Image: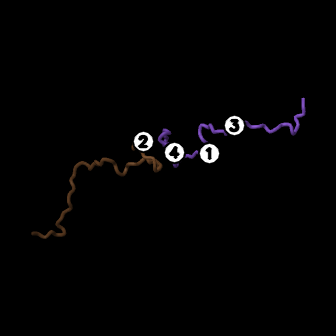
Chain colours: A purple, B brown
Amino acid sequence: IEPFLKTTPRPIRLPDGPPCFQRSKFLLMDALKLSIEDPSHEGEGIPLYDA
Amino acid sequence: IEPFLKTTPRPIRLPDGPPCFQRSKFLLMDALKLSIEDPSHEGEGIPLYDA
């Protein structure tokens, strides 16, 4: 055994190399949405036509 | 000539026979309308689907 001392754990070094790049299937902050402006309640829609 | 006197013109006699019957292409007082409840302004509709 050893004393897992206060000053012992060094800061974990992150890898270095090229910059990290996004891989999400859909962007998250920069996206925006073209509203429909509140259709009726009985009118169902096959989604293409609403789009 | 003759004097078209005040008392001369008898009341025109309407014909007599069976009762008069409607022939309009669409009834007029008794009809009613199933509303759509105010759709949007951009959504055009081929009329069957609105009906």
Do the CB atoms of the residues marked 3 and 1 lie less than 8 Å apart?
no
In the rendered structure, the residue with mark 3 lies on which chain? Answer: A
Label 1 or label 2, whichever lies nearer to me, is 1
Q: Which amino acid, mark 3?
A: Gly
Please rate how many residues cluster around mark 3, counting C-alpha atoms within 10 Å: few if below 14, some from 14 to 19, many from 20: few
Are tags 4 and 3 found on a single chain? yes
In the rendered structure, the residue with mark 2 lies on which chain? Answer: B
Q: Which amino acid, mark 4?
A: His
Which comes before the other along the chain, label 3 or label 1?
3
Residue occupying the point 62% across, 45% down = A29
Q: Position of residue B32 (x, y in %)?
A: 40, 48
Which residue matches tag 4? A41
- In three-dimensional space, the C-alpha distance between marks 4 and 3, rounded to whole angstroms, equals 54 Å
Label 3 or label 2, whichever lies nearer to me, is 3
Q: Is residue B1 left or right of residue A47?
A: left
Are tags 4 and 2 found on a single chain? no
Label 4 or label 3, whichever lies nearer to me, is 3
